[PDB]
Length: 150
Ligand SMILES: O=C(O)c1ccccc1O
Ligand SMILES: O=C(O)c1ccccc1O
Ligand SMILES: O=C(O)c1ccccc1O
Ligand SMILES: O=C(O)c1ccccc1O
Image (cartoon, rainbow, N blue to C red; front, side, top):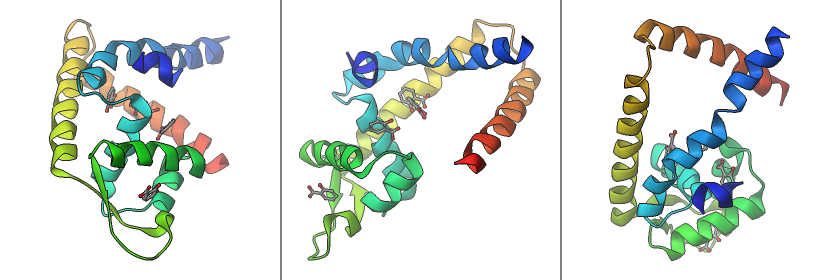
């Protein structure tokens, strides 16, 4: 439900990494479900974890989602006691956001499970550390272009 909720050489090349996304999320889905959190929620949670104290404004910008989407997901994170909002009289979109203790516990647990699952996947392949850094090198080049464009 989580993965479901979330929804030429150059051609074979792009296909090789774009088609891995969905299978990847299906496999990591249970990690989030076990913590009663959905993928959209996890991404914003993680984002806050790494940038807190942060704001709906900054979040929307780094995540590249629309305010309505970010507002709705944050609202669920708050309602679930995973993040706390600075109490202020300013606009909600300007208020500082940080993880609650429950939020941190959930975060550390998901993060470690994901890390171990990734290690496992790799361990079943013939991929070398070198092959991994070379891939990283190529992907970041692609990523630079897609972002500078936007
Ligand atoms: O950046 C993503 O789109 C993403 C999606 C699901 C899980 C981890 C991720 O980084
Ligand atoms: O970083 C990921 O690839 C990831 C995947 C599934 C759930 C949480 C995550 O951070
Ligand atoms: O990637 C995100 O930060 C995200 C968050 C909520 C809903 C959809 C999304 O892609
Ligand atoms: O509902 C809130 O308290 C809230 C707080 C910060 C950002 C968006 C929000 O909906």
